Image 1 (spheres, helix red, strand yellow):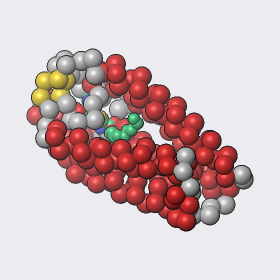
Image 2 (image 1 turned 180 degrees about the vertical axis):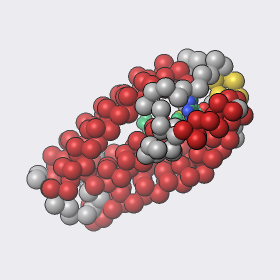
Image 3 (image 1 turned 180 degrees about the horizontal axis):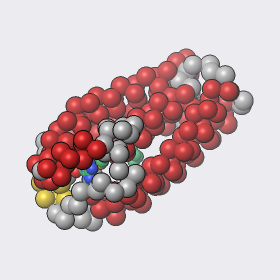
Length: 192
Ligand SMILES: Nc1ncnc2c1ncn2[C@@H]1O[C@H](CSCC[C@H](N)C(=O)O)[C@@H](O)[C@H]1O
């Protein structure tokens, strides 16, 4: 109930959410790049979310600035998020482990890149995104603030929406038919 509390909660899930990536990422950044794509652009699109995921909500916690925009939400609906975010971080570490040396945020195609249909990736390509999709939906409700809610959602949806079709096109360049088959056998976010 205490508001100062939820902040302490989130800044943890976050702190750990970040830890999960900081671990798996530096591991796959030690693998050299082959072809990148419009990276000077994606970088910004990312950094755009970087506001949405981190810079922005960090300041719904460590600062009172955004206070007037928060949603005055009942504790019931907030916990519902806190649960799901938990499940998320699992899924994250699931996904993120399933991916490993292939991951980047910029559309890299890595030197030894191997296409993975096998993991949480069977029946879902871009699970990670679907994760992120949730991530932004949840953290707004958890933090119960409209800006942190509304903004974050947008900045992703965009990056998402203009991101994915190049990504798919890109993977098709490299893997050719193996990817077209894949998409037939998979959905983008939910399965089937
Ligand atoms: N199905 C796949 N198998 C292996 N690498 C993939 C992949 N889909 C995307 N990638 C790589 O992953 C990087 C983006 S990370 C995003 C991965 C996936 N879209 C997800 O959200 O779960 C891109 O550089 C792309 O080269």
